[PDB]
Image 1: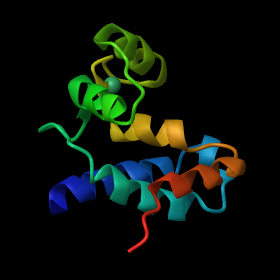
Image 2 (image 1 turned 90 degrees about the vertical axis):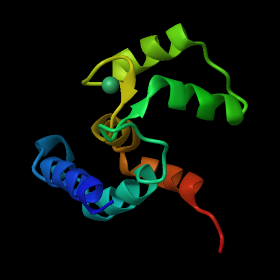
Image 3 (image 1 turned 30 degrees about the vertical axis):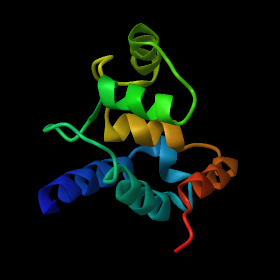
Image 4 (image 1 turned 120 degrees about the vertical axis):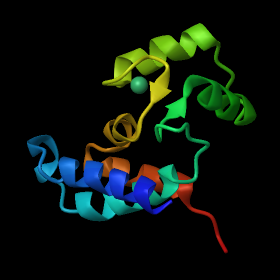
Length: 111
Ligand SMILES: [Ca+2]
């Protein structure tokens, strides 16, 4: 919805002021594209990907992980609980070295 998107945009703006990313000339464009994609996931009423949803996706992609294993994984990359993969967690994971820009083709789907 519109509110869900403004929230993510709010987080993007948050990231557009964070120094650890000011050095990326594509950050603005990346954030818009990651926002769109994130909007496609099965999110909870709080706008996050809960661990159960994450487990389902990883199993469907052929890379199964146990509940505990994902908690342990999420805990190390998240700023929130080990039971949620938030949009910001999503961003921190995806962003970084401009060479990581190539990873974005994983989202590409021909129309
Ligand atoms: Ca979390």
